[PDB]
Amino acid sequence: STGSATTTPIDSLDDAYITPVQIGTPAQTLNLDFDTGSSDLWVFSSETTASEVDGQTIYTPSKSTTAKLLSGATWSISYGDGSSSSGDVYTDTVSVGGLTVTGQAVESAKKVSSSFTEDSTIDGLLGLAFSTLNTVSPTQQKTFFDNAKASLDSPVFTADLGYHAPGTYNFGFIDTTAYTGSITYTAVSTKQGFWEWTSTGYAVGSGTFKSTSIDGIADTGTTLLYLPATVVSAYWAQVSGAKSSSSVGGYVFPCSATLPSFTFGVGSARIVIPGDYIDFGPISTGSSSCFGGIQSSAGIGINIFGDVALKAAFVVFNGATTPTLGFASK
Image (cartoon, rainbow, N blue to C red; front, side, top):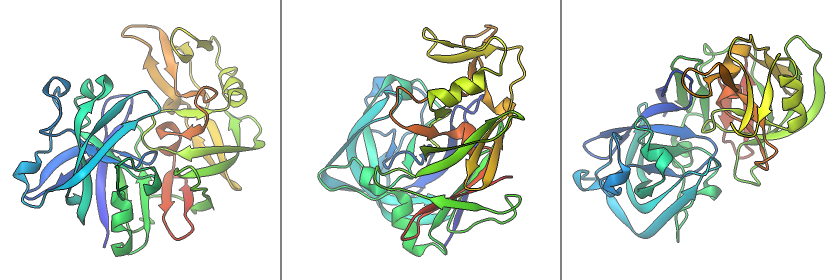
């Protein structure tokens, strides 16, 4: 089997992407944030504290003839941005772009933190990291991809995120029309549960490529590109007036600037992030200070190849017995 679904930016900045997902019988369609940095499929639901729902579409398990309470199971998750959610668990039928999994753990939120409430466009998350990170207790649950893998034509999914435009998540096949040149594959460590890999270096604008190993994670659920402070300083030093602002929480730059591109290495190959992809717009409405899309990871503990980087590429998440990542230009 295969599946193919369009993923759409939630706003004019590409802060996140939502993909429609059918849950239950009859189908209830929710728009979920596909997140290769986590491993829980959780939804706003009829069980979510009413004051914490503000415009999201909810899953109502009592209206699904295929929903079954996973008795005793609870979940609770905290994300790198400080947001969180928790609740109980049903199993139900879940379909993405025509690919159907029966018995998928659907984690029903009883509580969500304010950032989720405040984002009316995201009805939940669909985790695509390794199932070892799934938070369901006492019986850890598998991701949608893990459950689907055996049925897929090939044990892969691909992320093709758009810049200010829709893109595609495919399951079970590699669309050879969706990228240019060849796909370069690189090793993955699953030791932390992430799609963790080592970039071979970087370049700023037309500058020379610096060969240096940068370990990080391919994370569709993180907006920006988070890299070591040395690398980020070298990038922003090429932008007149750019500075790190403790009050804003990162590098800002004059909105009048034209940003240089940023290149990252995948083996001997190179992925170029156009400068425009690094512009996240005014820090507050009407400001002439703009927020940068490349930020330091120094306070995180891990480097994160988030959407800023991934949307410059066609990305293969290869879930073969030894997982690997593939990147192609597009």
